[PDB]
Structures are given as C-alpha cells and as structure tokens.
Length: 474
Ligand SMILES: [Zn+2]
Image 1 (cartoon, helix red, strand yellow):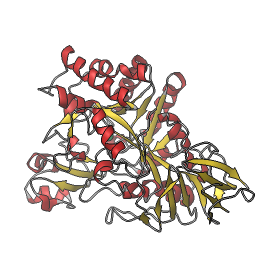
Image 2: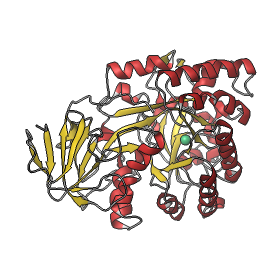
Image 3: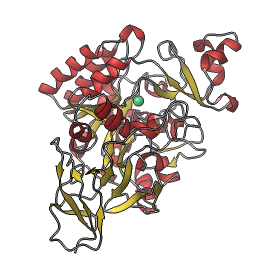
Image 4: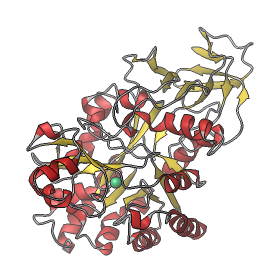
C-alpha cells in the first residue's frame, strides 16, 4: 500500500505542461504513481482539492551553507515550498577553511567561529550526520579556496597556490561537491586572473560538475564579464551557470535586452544557464562601490555599530558628513540591501525562457532582504498569476524541472513515478510572498504542505520536526 495519496488536486508536474487533475501516491521516499489512484490502497488519502501538487522547489542560488548546520529546520526555505538548496555560491563556501575571521563576503555565512571545516568532506559529513529539512547540493567556492591557501589575496595566485587550490577543489568534488563557484567581483578574488580560475576549475570535467559564477562585473563592464564567463566555459568544457543575472545601475537600465541576447547566442554553441531573484534590490556585504551605493541602501547588520542594523545608509552617511561611498570603511564589516535594478529588466530576465529561480537569501542577516522568505511564492503569485508574466506551469518549471536538469539532480524536480517525493501542495489562487522590505521575515501565503523525500517537513504553517534532507550528488 502507498503511505499516502495527495488526492483531488491539480498536478503541475515540472515538465512545463498545463496542470491536470490527478492524484499523487507516495511510498517511502518515492512517488509511486500519478493519475486516478482511487484503486490503489493507501494508508492515508489526503484531500488537496483546489490545490496544486508540484515538485518541491529547488533554490537556484543560496548562501545556506552554514544555515543548514545551525538551523536545521530551514524555515525560511521550507515555508516557501523549497525542498532542495544549491549552496556554495559566488565563490563563497563554508568549507574548506578553518578561520576565525574570514574575509568579507565570506562573513555572510558566519555566526561566530563557523568556519571550522578544514576539508570539504568534513562539512558534508556533518550535514549527513545531522540532516537539515531540505536536500543540499553543495559547491565549493574559489574565494574560500583562496582564503585557505593564499597568504596574500591581493594578487594572482602562483602555480604552487593554484596547485593547492586545485587539490582542495578536486577533493571536494570527489567527496560529493557538485561544482565550483567564483565571485571575482569580491575583494578576495578581484585579483584572480581568468587563467587562475580555469586552472583551479579543471577537475570539473573529470567529476562532471558545473561552474557557477557571480560575474566579475554586472554593470558597465557586464559584456566583458559575460565574455569572460563564456570563455571559461569553453576552456573547462563544462556547463556554466550565471548567478543572479541583472544589469545594475541607472547607466545600465534596459541593458537586459543586450545581455540576454548575448546569453541566448552563447547557449546555441555551449552549455549556459542562469538564475535570478524576483526583486529590484540586491544584498551582500557593505562594499565601497560607486554603483551599489548610488541609490537607496539599507544596512542589514553591522559589526562595529550594531545599532545601525535596519537603517538607511544615506542618513548614516549624511549625519557623519560623508557620501555613502566615503562612510563605508568605518562601518565595515557590515551587510546591506542595494536598490540598484529596474523592474523592466527584472521582468525581462525572469521571463527569458532559460532563467531559473534562485532566492539569494542571506539567512544570517539581522534585517534581511525579503527574498530570503518570499522568492518562490513571489514568482508563482505576483508574477505568474497577478501580472501574467508566464503561465503557472512555466513558473513552476523554472523552479523545478529546469533547475533539476541544469544541476544534474537526478530523479528530482518532476512529479513522475519513480522520482523522489519532494513535493509542494499550494493554493494557486492565494500563493503569495508576504515578506516585504519593511517585514522581511513574514511567511508566505498559500503554501499548504511541503514534502522532502516523502516526509512532510512543512504542515499547518510549522516545521514538522522531520530532518528529511539528503546531501545530493550530480
Ligand atoms: Zn553573488
């Protein structure tokens, strides 16, 4: 007999097909059957009339590396329907690095002494021994590798340093990492050359992993950064994933037309993917950057002056008699939210066929960007239903089947017999992001229940206590 059947709802199967009335039966960690299951014995037949049963949402871009260890409930994600997270993005991974004061932006993962894993395998073992509520597909970050190996980050790595970093990356992949990410936009890797990145990432071909990247620049020089990324992909001969695609700064508004055209052209000749979050503001370390600081900027946390959390940086700066750019050093380390994108570009990028959804949530932040709690329902409700940017099945595909295919997460991302029972039950009419910039931790509406490997992890608007997630391999 099946353990349970989600009966009477509409199945949106993750393959980008209009929903159809069908039941979903689960046995253990697997979807046993899909269709009219009235004739199948089941221990429970759960009524989900009026709801959609879809595959669990796979987050396209997280910084949950440490959150998985410290807050196993993973409430910000499971409350949104997320069942799997891709970690170790933008060159930032929790492991391998034993360091009491890692360089920003690695601090976005730190709760205080969190960087304690000398080997990547140590980190994966900790996850497997105390599993989180969601599955984890983990990448190793090139900036973490530089921090672990280089005595001086302000220059290109020597061959010896490249050898040490490549060895750590190869061990990580052998242990289960699904790829390597870079973020040369950030200080720890700003001096890394294209060749350094290529040499450290060589093992991806041998292990069948992916190359993910926070491009070197996402503004004035985004074409050069895209070309660098495509070149790295061709040299590595592995799939590339462009993280949180955007065009930032007023001088670049509207340029999504140009960037998406370059990406679409590259996709015709090499393997390229991209993801994005559904908002007009970014968030990361507080950084002295003319473009990030051009517009409205809010502080998310601040080490030297904790009282600044939540404040408007222009006010802080002006009261200190400085521009935002000049006041930044005295406030570091800190985090911020930057209103530097334009709605038409965000919509064009979200609607671009291949764009996967990634929240880019920064879970340890005191006053976080709402994308941490509202990304997926914002796409399903606001964008799909309310604005009609894409039909619901396409919005679901962009956070399920597409993502599972690009990251190579076998037997996940689709409601198919034999696949793992990572599932979401949501009300298409009411699903909505409730988190706002003012109240960024509000739980989404319309998420009825969420299942990971067949076990309910979210029910009655609460974590069930099921630590059902698994560390995944490509
Ligand atoms: Zn990034």
